[PDB]
Image (cartoon, coloured by chain):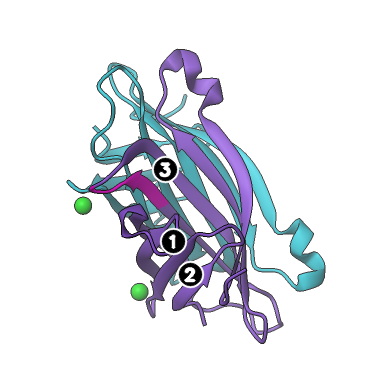
Chain colours: A purple, B cyan
Amino acid sequence: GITGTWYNQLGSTFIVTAGADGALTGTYESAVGNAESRYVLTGRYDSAPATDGSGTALGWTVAWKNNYRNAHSATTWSGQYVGGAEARINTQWLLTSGTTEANAXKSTLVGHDTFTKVKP
Amino acid sequence: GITGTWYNQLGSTFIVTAGADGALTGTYESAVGNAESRYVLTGRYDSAPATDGSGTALGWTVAWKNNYRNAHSATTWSGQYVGGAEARINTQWLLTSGTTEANAXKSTLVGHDTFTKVKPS
Ligand SMILES: [Cl-]
Ligand SMILES: [Cl-]
Protein backbone atom coordinates (compact mmCIF):
# COMPACT_ATOMS: atom_id res chain seq x y z
CA GLY A 1 0.00 0.00 0.00
CA ILE A 2 3.04 2.29 0.25
CA THR A 3 4.10 2.24 -3.41
CA GLY A 4 2.78 5.23 -5.31
CA THR A 5 2.36 8.98 -5.03
CA TRP A 6 1.80 10.89 -1.80
CA TYR A 7 1.07 14.54 -1.07
CA ASN A 8 1.83 16.50 2.08
CA GLN A 9 -0.55 19.23 3.19
CA LEU A 10 1.56 22.14 1.90
CA GLY A 11 2.26 21.48 -1.79
CA SER A 12 4.97 18.81 -1.83
CA THR A 13 4.71 15.36 -3.32
CA PHE A 14 6.72 12.24 -3.52
CA ILE A 15 6.62 9.03 -5.52
CA VAL A 16 8.00 5.92 -3.85
CA THR A 17 8.45 2.25 -4.65
CA ALA A 18 8.40 -0.14 -1.69
CA GLY A 19 10.60 -3.14 -2.42
CA ALA A 20 9.66 -6.61 -1.23
CA ASP A 21 12.46 -6.74 1.37
CA GLY A 22 12.16 -3.26 2.87
CA ALA A 23 13.68 -0.78 0.40
CA LEU A 24 12.14 2.62 -0.27
CA THR A 25 13.26 4.35 -3.47
CA GLY A 26 11.80 7.29 -5.32
CA THR A 27 11.69 11.03 -5.90
CA TYR A 28 10.62 13.93 -3.67
CA GLU A 29 9.30 17.13 -5.28
CA SER A 30 9.15 20.15 -2.98
CA ALA A 31 6.69 21.92 -5.32
CA VAL A 32 4.11 19.88 -7.22
CA GLY A 33 4.59 20.39 -10.94
CA ASN A 34 8.10 21.94 -10.72
CA ALA A 35 10.57 19.41 -12.09
CA GLU A 36 13.53 21.50 -10.91
CA SER A 37 12.42 20.76 -7.33
CA ARG A 38 12.80 16.95 -7.70
CA TYR A 39 15.32 15.11 -5.49
CA VAL A 40 16.32 11.49 -4.89
CA LEU A 41 14.61 9.74 -1.94
CA THR A 42 15.92 6.57 -0.28
CA GLY A 43 14.78 4.81 2.87
CA ARG A 44 13.50 1.67 4.58
CA TYR A 45 10.22 0.25 5.85
CA ASP A 46 9.05 -2.74 7.87
CA SER A 47 8.16 -5.25 5.16
CA ALA A 48 6.36 -7.56 7.64
CA PRO A 49 4.21 -5.24 9.78
CA ALA A 50 1.95 -6.39 12.58
CA THR A 51 -1.50 -7.59 11.56
CA ASP A 52 -3.28 -6.08 14.59
CA GLY A 53 -4.21 -2.79 12.90
CA SER A 54 -0.92 -1.09 13.77
CA GLY A 55 0.76 1.16 11.24
CA THR A 56 3.82 0.20 9.22
CA ALA A 57 7.02 1.90 10.40
CA LEU A 58 9.21 3.60 7.79
CA GLY A 59 11.72 6.38 7.21
CA TRP A 60 13.49 8.07 4.33
CA THR A 61 16.08 10.74 3.54
CA VAL A 62 16.34 13.48 0.91
CA ALA A 63 19.63 15.31 0.48
CA TRP A 64 18.69 18.68 -1.02
CA LYS A 65 21.08 18.52 -3.97
CA ASN A 66 20.00 18.09 -7.57
CA ASN A 67 21.11 19.59 -10.87
CA TYR A 68 19.46 22.94 -10.09
CA ARG A 69 20.06 23.49 -6.38
CA ASN A 70 22.31 22.51 -3.50
CA ALA A 71 20.99 23.66 -0.13
CA HIS A 72 23.77 21.76 1.69
CA SER A 73 21.21 20.08 3.89
CA ALA A 74 19.24 16.88 4.23
CA THR A 75 15.85 15.97 5.70
CA THR A 76 14.83 12.66 7.28
CA TRP A 77 11.21 11.66 7.78
CA SER A 78 10.33 9.08 10.43
CA GLY A 79 6.80 7.76 10.65
CA GLN A 80 4.23 5.11 9.90
CA TYR A 81 1.93 4.16 7.04
CA VAL A 82 -1.74 3.50 7.82
CA GLY A 83 -3.78 1.95 5.01
CA GLY A 84 -7.46 1.91 4.19
CA ALA A 85 -9.99 4.43 2.94
CA GLU A 86 -8.07 7.54 4.03
CA ALA A 87 -4.60 6.04 3.84
CA ARG A 88 -1.93 8.27 5.37
CA ILE A 89 1.75 8.39 6.17
CA ASN A 90 2.16 10.33 9.41
CA THR A 91 5.68 11.64 9.95
CA GLN A 92 8.01 13.78 11.90
CA TRP A 93 11.06 15.22 10.20
CA LEU A 94 14.54 16.55 10.95
CA LEU A 95 16.27 18.96 8.55
CA THR A 96 20.02 19.29 9.17
CA SER A 97 22.16 21.91 7.41
CA GLY A 98 25.90 21.66 7.09
CA THR A 99 27.26 24.33 9.46
CA THR A 100 30.46 25.60 10.95
CA GLU A 101 31.27 24.24 14.39
CA ALA A 102 30.32 27.61 15.89
CA ASN A 103 26.84 27.33 14.34
CA ALA A 104 26.33 23.61 15.02
CA UNK A 105 23.58 24.35 17.60
CA LYS A 106 21.54 25.98 14.85
CA SER A 107 21.93 23.00 12.53
CA THR A 108 18.68 21.00 12.87
CA LEU A 109 15.05 22.02 12.34
CA VAL A 110 12.19 19.76 13.39
CA GLY A 111 8.66 19.47 12.11
CA HIS A 112 5.91 17.14 10.94
CA ASP A 113 4.21 16.11 7.70
CA THR A 114 1.03 14.18 7.01
CA PHE A 115 0.99 12.54 3.57
CA THR A 116 -2.21 11.50 1.81
CA LYS A 117 -3.02 9.87 -1.51
CA VAL A 118 -5.08 12.93 -2.57
CA LYS A 119 -4.05 16.58 -2.72
CA PRO A 120 -4.98 19.00 0.11
CA GLY B 1 35.67 10.83 4.45
CA ILE B 2 32.29 9.25 5.20
CA THR B 3 32.94 5.76 3.81
CA GLY B 4 33.98 3.34 6.52
CA THR B 5 33.12 2.25 10.03
CA TRP B 6 31.69 4.50 12.73
CA TYR B 7 30.93 3.94 16.42
CA ASN B 8 28.41 5.72 18.58
CA GLN B 9 29.17 6.31 22.22
CA LEU B 10 27.02 3.45 23.57
CA GLY B 11 28.18 0.29 21.79
CA SER B 12 26.65 0.50 18.30
CA THR B 13 28.51 0.53 15.02
CA PHE B 14 27.78 1.03 11.41
CA ILE B 15 29.66 0.55 8.16
CA VAL B 16 28.67 2.81 5.29
CA THR B 17 29.70 3.40 1.69
CA ALA B 18 29.21 6.91 0.34
CA GLY B 19 28.48 6.80 -3.38
CA ALA B 20 29.81 9.45 -5.72
CA ASP B 21 26.38 11.02 -6.36
CA GLY B 22 24.97 11.02 -2.83
CA ALA B 23 23.98 7.44 -1.90
CA LEU B 24 24.59 6.00 1.56
CA THR B 25 24.46 2.20 1.80
CA GLY B 26 25.63 -0.09 4.55
CA THR B 27 24.87 -2.06 7.70
CA TYR B 28 24.00 -0.89 11.23
CA GLU B 29 24.87 -3.17 14.18
CA SER B 30 23.14 -2.29 17.46
CA ALA B 31 25.73 -4.29 19.45
CA VAL B 32 29.37 -4.49 18.36
CA GLY B 33 30.36 -8.03 17.43
CA ASN B 34 26.79 -9.43 17.53
CA ALA B 35 25.94 -10.31 13.95
CA GLU B 36 22.29 -11.00 14.85
CA SER B 37 21.97 -7.26 15.56
CA ARG B 38 22.92 -6.22 11.99
CA TYR B 39 20.38 -4.32 9.86
CA VAL B 40 20.32 -2.70 6.42
CA LEU B 41 21.09 1.06 6.34
CA THR B 42 20.16 3.34 3.43
CA GLY B 43 20.35 7.11 3.12
CA ARG B 44 21.66 10.20 1.35
CA TYR B 45 24.38 12.81 1.78
CA ASP B 46 25.40 16.09 0.16
CA SER B 47 28.03 14.97 -2.35
CA ALA B 48 29.19 18.58 -3.00
CA PRO B 49 29.50 20.15 0.46
CA ALA B 50 30.63 23.68 1.13
CA THR B 51 34.40 24.15 1.30
CA ASP B 52 34.22 26.84 4.02
CA GLY B 53 34.74 24.43 6.92
CA SER B 54 31.04 23.56 7.19
CA GLY B 55 29.98 19.99 7.84
CA THR B 56 28.47 17.68 5.24
CA ALA B 57 24.72 17.11 5.70
CA LEU B 58 23.47 13.52 5.61
CA GLY B 59 20.72 11.22 6.83
CA TRP B 60 19.91 7.53 6.89
CA THR B 61 17.23 5.05 7.93
CA VAL B 62 17.29 1.60 9.56
CA ALA B 63 14.11 -0.45 9.68
CA TRP B 64 14.56 -2.79 12.66
CA LYS B 65 13.79 -6.00 10.79
CA ASN B 66 16.35 -8.67 9.97
CA ASN B 67 16.34 -12.47 10.01
CA TYR B 68 16.45 -12.58 13.82
CA ARG B 69 14.21 -9.74 14.98
CA ASN B 70 11.38 -7.49 13.88
CA ALA B 71 10.73 -4.61 16.27
CA HIS B 72 8.15 -3.11 13.88
CA SER B 73 9.92 0.22 14.03
CA ALA B 74 12.40 2.35 12.12
CA THR B 75 14.98 4.96 13.12
CA THR B 76 16.17 7.92 11.04
CA TRP B 77 19.36 9.82 11.79
CA SER B 78 19.79 13.39 10.58
CA GLY B 79 23.10 15.15 10.96
CA GLN B 80 26.40 16.25 9.52
CA TYR B 81 29.85 14.79 8.97
CA VAL B 82 32.86 16.82 10.14
CA GLY B 83 36.25 15.61 8.96
CA GLY B 84 39.76 16.02 10.27
CA ALA B 85 41.78 14.55 13.11
CA GLU B 86 38.76 13.82 15.29
CA ALA B 87 36.24 13.20 12.53
CA ARG B 88 32.68 12.83 13.72
CA ILE B 89 29.12 12.45 12.52
CA ASN B 90 26.85 14.44 14.83
CA THR B 91 23.22 13.35 14.64
CA GLN B 92 19.75 13.54 16.02
CA TRP B 93 17.42 10.60 15.58
CA LEU B 94 13.73 9.73 15.46
CA LEU B 95 12.54 6.19 16.28
CA THR B 96 8.97 5.49 15.13
CA SER B 97 7.09 2.32 16.10
CA GLY B 98 4.09 1.04 14.23
CA THR B 99 1.14 1.68 16.59
CA THR B 100 -2.61 1.55 16.74
CA GLU B 101 -4.33 4.84 16.05
CA ALA B 102 -5.14 5.20 19.75
CA ASN B 103 -1.42 4.88 20.57
CA ALA B 104 -0.15 7.06 17.70
CA UNK B 105 0.88 9.86 20.11
CA LYS B 106 3.30 7.44 21.74
CA SER B 107 4.83 6.43 18.42
CA THR B 108 8.06 8.45 18.09
CA LEU B 109 11.10 8.66 20.38
CA VAL B 110 13.78 11.31 19.86
CA GLY B 111 17.44 11.33 20.76
CA HIS B 112 20.97 11.99 19.56
CA ASP B 113 24.10 10.07 18.61
CA THR B 114 27.69 11.15 18.10
CA PHE B 115 29.64 8.79 15.83
CA THR B 116 33.44 8.61 15.83
CA LYS B 117 36.04 6.60 13.94
CA VAL B 118 37.30 4.95 17.18
CA LYS B 119 35.38 3.15 19.90
CA PRO B 120 34.30 4.84 23.14
CA SER B 121 36.26 3.87 26.24
CL1 LIG C 1 13.64 -4.56 -1.23
CL1 LIG D 1 25.78 7.48 -5.61
Q: Residue furthest top?
A: A102
Amino acid on which disc 1 is placed: Glu
Q: Position of residue B8 (x, y in %)?
A: 46, 35
Residue underneath mark 2: B68
**Magenta portion: prevailing SS class:** strand
Q: Return the residue nearer the eye: A111 or B73.
A: A111
Secondary structure found at label 3: strand
Q: Are marks 3 and 2 in contact (CB under 8 Å)?
A: no
- Ligand 2 closer than 8 Å to the CB at disc 3? no
Q: Secondary structure at mark 2?
A: loop
- What's the residue at 40%, 51% (across, down)? A62
Q: Which chain letter goes with mark 2?
A: B
Quadrant of the image occupied by residue B98:
bottom right
For disc 3, the marked residue is A74
Segment colored magenta? A62-67
Query: Does A5 appear above or below A104?
Result: below
Give the mark toward the camera: 3 or 1: 3
Nearer to me, B9 or B19: B19
At 28% from the left edge and 16% from the top edge, which residue is drawn? B85
